[PDB]
Image (cartoon, rainbow, N blue to C red; front, side, top):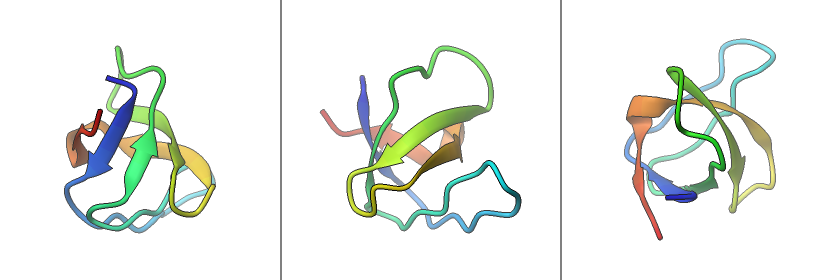
Length: 59
């Protein structure tokens, strides 16, 4: 899986995390380790870290 969909809204809290809305689709090329995965929004074009438990597959 390299494209994912948000299950919940997330508001960013620091300089490295990415805000996103429930249903927003995210490209995530590395999801093999950690609680935070680097994601790129297919909606907004913004990029940053998202919580691993906030997304489900979308490809």
